[PDB]
Length: 295
Length: 126
Length: 112
Ligand SMILES: *[C@@H]1O[C@H](CO)[C@@H](O[C@@H]2O[C@H](CO)[C@@H](O)[C@H](O)[C@H]2NC(C)=O)[C@H](O)[C@H]1NC(C)=O
Ligand SMILES: *[C@@H]1O[C@H](CO)[C@@H](O[C@@H]2O[C@H](CO)[C@@H](O)[C@H](O)[C@H]2NC(C)=O)[C@H](O)[C@H]1NC(C)=O
Ligand SMILES: *[C@@H]1O[C@H](CO)[C@@H](O[C@@H]2O[C@H](CO)[C@@H](O)[C@H](O)[C@H]2NC(C)=O)[C@H](O)[C@H]1NC(C)=O
Ligand SMILES: *[C@@H]1O[C@H](CO)[C@@H](O)[C@H](O)[C@H]1NC(C)=O
Ligand SMILES: *[C@@H]1O[C@H](CO)[C@@H](O)[C@H](O)[C@H]1NC(C)=O
Ligand SMILES: *[C@@H]1O[C@H](CO)[C@@H](O)[C@H](O)[C@H]1NC(C)=O
Ligand SMILES: *[C@@H]1O[C@H](CO)[C@@H](O)[C@H](O)[C@H]1NC(C)=O
Image 1 (cartoon, each protein chain N blue to C red):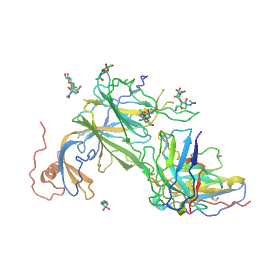
Image 2: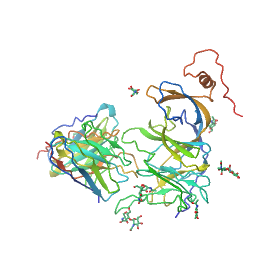
Image 3: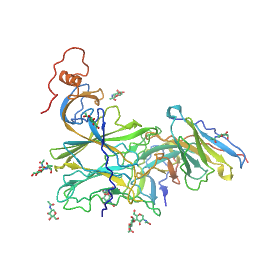
Image 4: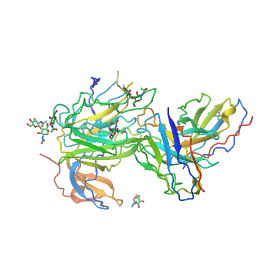
């Protein structure tokens, strides 16, 4: 059973800058003290990301956006609202659907032909007499039908909490769809009460390499709502950006982890740094390989 | 009703292995991570180890010399301290307590401090 | 880790007022605590998780008599109109990255 709880408020998406976010490890080999150059789907530095936040002010919004080539995800978290996604192509009818979910202790991955209503949510019920809270609710899909794939593992979204103060749980994700393999990268970084993508660097670790092979064009993010304007609750804000085919140059530190990445298509200084393969450049003339224009 | 009952006492020479448990009922374990606390006789209580809701373990507090191990069987609705290598100082009460931060929470995260405590068991070791 | 300079013995008259003190290391000035009362020969009882601003989160069966206050990097628990049951051990504990702390306990020999 599902219900028309839209209460959608229309506001323009406040485009904001990520400042050198969205880079991951391109390969599964331990290098160190090297400047390996790679060409892969990466979020470009100083790129427009979409600040989506449906809360504060009964403002609820959760539109269907295009997976394009990849989807950089962030989830500055306060009270565990973002619970998963429903990647797919049509998200209804007779087509194949993906229902990436992060449960209370595990991660359930199902690629199947689910039917979806317009406003999917996960509803948690709290009782006074027994106090047990159960996820025994399913309103993202009405039912499931002629199903193909199921996967249970350790959950992606991990607390990493217990520490105090102003630090926040910034949860980063990278989704890409290549050779029918939905690759998922993630890392979690504490941030000292920042209201914007932090000024630092990220190293997104590989999590799963799912052998799915399904068409994914219009993805969407699940949320969790309590019971209690029926079925409303929480507080959340997340940020979505898209990966494009670019070229980066990564410098590896002495621990084997990346320190900083120098893009090859934003600034003339970065193009010269890319075409000379070094992170320090002196004064002079540096002929640059051509990455400025793409037809 | 929330309650934390334990069992698995025993007298052994140092280096022996026993079976400690914290059975509970009346509330969800899936969304509650559990801690362990050690209280030497006449001394202050000191936590030893804990397991998270997902399944990750922390054998911290540097009093455990790689001797204590924690696990959990969510299927059987029970909580075990995977126990081996008891030593002389380990003769103490082992109050197991349930943290206030359940996984489906609101408000500020002034939680993970224990709201309830088990009755505790005395595991005498010499 | 943080150390608690809580007096091993503090006392006052019954029906009077006292103030317990939980001291905390300067490195974690804005850190919060929670108070556990360990009545002797029984289990611990949780009173309040004290915010850095003195806000309250209360356990069952504890009246408004037991209250908490904060000032600087150190913390207080307030008791007014003392009764017979106060002779017990009080433990102030904290949070970290997987590292609880707890304290020596506040054996309290309220004379009366
Ligand atoms: C969410 O996690 C819970 C675990 O507490 C799952 O509940 C059981 O999960 C196992 C394996 O995942 C199944 O074999 C059982 O049949 C489940 N019992 C139930 C649902 O009562 C649950 O499957 C997970 N997924 C969802 C969507 O709730
Ligand atoms: C305590 O919780 C359990 C589930 O964790 C309840 O069992 C079901 O609770 C749901 C509440 O959403 C009811 O709709 C079902 O009818 C219950 N099942 C059965 C077989 O009755 C249980 O009822 C709860 N205890 C209460 C409400 O006193
Ligand atoms: C993957 O999905 C896209 C989107 O549904 C498919 O593109 C459609 O292809 C049909 C082919 O007749 C066209 O009529 C539609 O106009 C296309 N729609 C869009 C939005 O492009 C695509 O063919 C699918 N298969 C791939 C990419 O191999
Ligand atoms: C990002 O969006 C803003 C409008 O919100 C726009 O002015 C800016 O040019 C965009 N960034 C880039 C690199 O175009
Ligand atoms: C799809 O479902 C129908 C029944 O709804 C079934 O007859 C058919 O075999 C299923 N096909 C696949 C590929 O699972
Ligand atoms: C890792 O980095 C830290 C600090 O940068 C350093 O102490 C250590 O030697 C490095 N290497 C390893 C193997 O830990
Ligand atoms: C702490 O205790 C002392 C003595 O009882 C008192 O002067 C002081 O006001 C107390 N502080 C608070 C915040 O109640």
